[PDB]
Amino acid sequence: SIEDQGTTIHGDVELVVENETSADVSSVLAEVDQIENNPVEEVLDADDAV
Amino acid sequence: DLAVIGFELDTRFTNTNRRQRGHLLQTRALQFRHPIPMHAPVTLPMDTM
Image 1 (tube, each protein chain N blue to C red):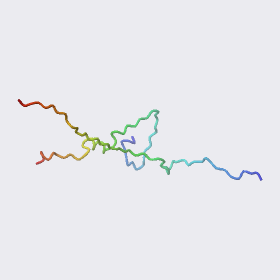
Image 2 (cartoon, each protein chain N blue to C red):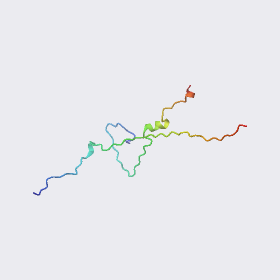
Image 3 (cartoon, rainbow over the protein chains, first blue to last red):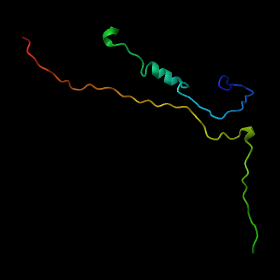
Image 4 (tube, rainbow over the protein chains, first blue to last red):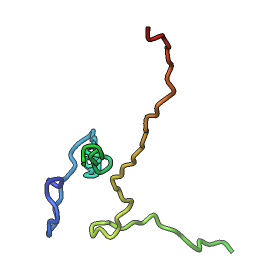
């Protein structure tokens, strides 16, 4: 499985035996997960941080 | 003076040594920011009595 592996020294090959292929990339980026957590670093309100 | 002088071929390499990459794909994301403003209120005055 090319998706699961990486840095394979001898390489690998898979044959695409398929007709209709879909690619959902909404969850691929790590930055998207970071933004969903907090678009900007979280800051406690000054009234509470004191 | 009539002769064939030249030709061109539709020859291509077999990219089995993966010399050529072709086009590249990379995953990207853009961010848009929409802050919500306040607007002026409407007031109903009444006496305190």
